[PDB]
Image 1 (tube, rainbow, N blue to C red):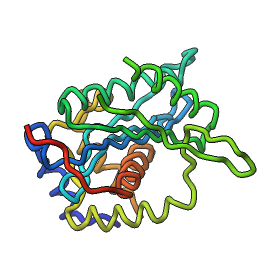
Image 2 (cartoon, rainbow, N blue to C red):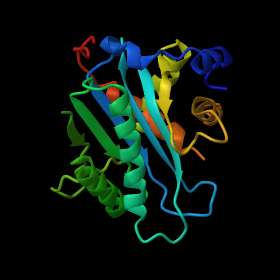
Image 3 (tube, one colour):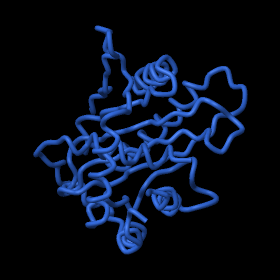
Length: 225
């Protein structure tokens, strides 16, 4: 019961309308993708979060809990198409708001598969805001790969999130985007069910890590239109 019920209820209910308060947003989007490369399993979901700064708080613009079709020949591109579709919708809902989107693809599962996802995201997004990837120089290597390795930074990320969430500093956009969590359950309600397991975690990890990335930060605001 790490996150208090009271903060959880407020997270569900009070959702700033981002499309009409764009002046309160920071001009950078942060996205984290926590991939699972299997199908026909309950822990085979890929988590995606796109978040940003709202005043000095953090707001979620989109969520995905994506399940590979079994025996596709293009799992990384299927995941990439999912994240690109999410981003696009977020971009279209807030036109001209963002100067940068920064994308982290967790590579713990497979570095090559994470790189492939980044490459497809890179290419598809090529059809304004600049797109950057988090890069990682694996131990013993001089190469900078466009994936993120989750290790020592997990405990600080979780610790900061819990403190921010409990004090009312993390919220969801009233016009939060989700293609994968729309028909069966409310995306914010679904995320909160995963979050209340703190003591399948792809969505929770993506959200907490996307926010941790945004939390290393700067000082301008999106324009007011």
